[PDB]
Amino acid sequence: GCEGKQCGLFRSCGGGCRCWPTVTPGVGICSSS
Image 1: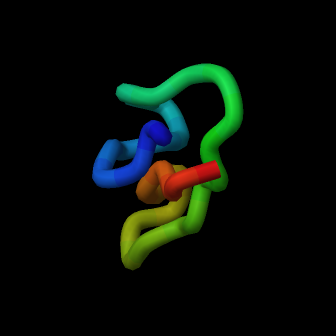
Image 2: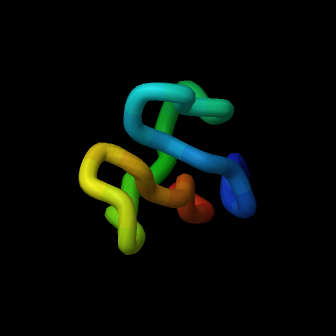
């Protein structure tokens, strides 16, 4: 639903998205749900 986005501090997603962390501490990616 809101996948392919960046989460964490600069979260470009909202609602029901999984915030999977990346290589940068505090930076992640928003998943489908």
